[PDB]
Image (cartoon, rainbow, N blue to C red):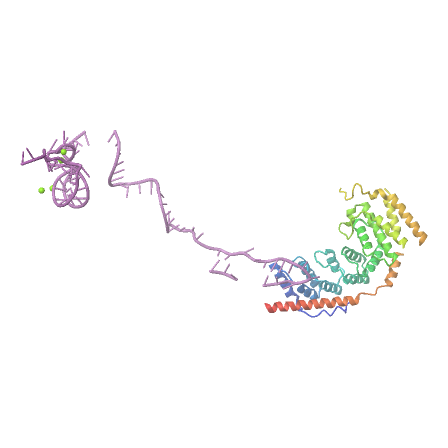
Length: 328
RNA sequence: GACUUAACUAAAACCCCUACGCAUUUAUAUAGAGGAGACGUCGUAACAUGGUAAGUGUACUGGAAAGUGCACUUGGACGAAC
Ligand SMILES: [Mg+2]
Ligand SMILES: [Mg+2]
Ligand SMILES: [Mg+2]
Ligand SMILES: [Mg+2]
């Protein structure tokens, strides 16, 4: 979805001069406008140039204007990356996050995901997904896509996972898992909860919430159970986890507040009961695929509007600059 | 005597050098010169009308006290009837 964007509007097409200016600004320890950065981003037309731009971005991030790094600039950068290589450099930036200060909580992410899908690369995609999760996102319908990707990854990834990875997986499951419309979403959520529960029990409660959008409160297994029950009112992995748990420093929890390692048999029983109920009443990848096939009516008008707004803003900025020059 | 960047949150940047010299001031230490104070010689200057009454000022003079001039003082006296 490229040709809607490629009316960028014209500016200066000399990068060396811009670079020099930037250096001078930094030499003096003076601030830099966002506009210049945007222009720089626009200009790029080589891998060396891309590298240079990256550096410049980093510098900006470490300056009196850490903020003002506008969405539009980020978008432009992403586009540039896509045009050239994309899957190493953008990813790297995302990983760095705080240093390049890119924070593209937008359709950019979706685009990136799509690109990744187009040229296989699974690990990278997973990483991207994780990064997105770490950022507070998931108002848009890319959530489904993310979930699908996660599922795909899981379909390959079937070992002991390990500390960070399990947590990441759980996070991925959870935040995109807000799909009240279908039982698949609920299942995903449950799975996520189970993973998180496992993490809690093996290692610690702090291990779960430390860096993630996740909440300190102890009952994760309980929460999962509740969620499951909700569905009934209106899994294998979870069972396995439970079984494992059953099989044979500071304290955030209280003396009165009961320890969840000493609530296991009861929990297991509850789970069993729930399962029975489900059976009485009455694959994941397939479901996800089906979902994908349905739905997906896009956000293109909105995107266009946003672009227009950005353009307007740019124009305003230019005008301001002109005024300043006149004054000078 | 020298002197702007940035503005979807708001912020960053912003740093001059020149007077002290055996110039000033006061004091200490001095080649040497001059007093004052303290403890034999030459006169006899003053004290008695002190042997030319004393003394003041000023002048000149003389080993030294002092001598003399001019004008002042009684801290001199003139004996207190003819
Ligand atoms: Mg005599
Ligand atoms: Mg006589
Ligand atoms: Mg004579
Ligand atoms: Mg004669």
